[PDB]
Image (cartoon, coloured by chain):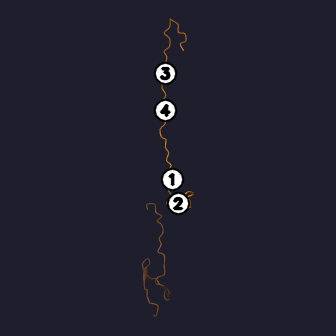
Chain colours: A orange, B brown
């Protein structure tokens, strides 16, 4: 804060401030999915008969 | 042979390494020259196709 150093002593020296780092590197996602080429033979729920 | 013709069919098909006759030893088929038959074909269930 400041507290009260008297005008007869030098006083203490404050450490200024600062210093904080961090890392958040990798991440990933990959939704592979199949087309199923033999699924197209039968009738889909759509595509009215 | 009268109203009917005589055709001797000695066709052969190859197995893995040997020959075999299309017809059995002793059979005959009463047929018609205009008898309609289907040479129908399926669908190619290939991904590239």
| Disc 3 with disc 1 on a shared chain | yes
In the picture of the structure, the residue carrying the numbered disc 2 is: A39
Residue at 42% from the left image edge and 83% from the top image edge:
B11
Q: Quick one: label 3 or label 4, which is nearer the N terminus?
A: 3
Residue at 51% from the left image edge and 53% from the top image edge:
A33
Mark number displayed over residue A33: 1
Q: Nearer the viewer, mark 1 or mark 2?
A: 2
Mark number displayed over residue A17: 3
In the picture of the structure, the residue carrying the numbered disc 4 is: A22
Q: Is A31 above or below relative to A17?
A: below
Q: Quick one: label 3 or label 1, which is nearer the N terminus?
A: 3
Q: Is B34 above or below relative to A29?
A: below
Q: Quick one: label 2 or label 4, which is nearer the N terminus?
A: 4
Q: Secondary structure at mark 2?
A: helix
Q: Secondary structure at mark 3?
A: loop
Distance CA(mark 3)–CA(mark 1): 52 Å
Q: Nearer the viewer, mark 2 or mark 3?
A: 2
- What chain does mark 1 sit on? A
């Amino acid at each position: 804060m400041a507290l009260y150093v008297s005008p007869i002593v030098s006083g203490e020296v404050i450490r200024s401030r600062g210093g904080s780092t961090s890392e958040f590197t990798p991440g990933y996602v990959k939704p592979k999915h199949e087309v199923n080429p033999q699924m197209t033979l039968r009738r889909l729920p759509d595509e009215d008969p | 042979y009268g109203d009917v013709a005589i055709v001797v069919y000695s066709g052969q098909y190859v197995e893995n390494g040997v020959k075999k006759n299309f017809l059995p030893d002793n059979t005959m088929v009463l047929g018609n020259t205009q008898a309609r038959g289907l040479r129908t074909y399926g669908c190619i269930q290939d991904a590239d196709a």
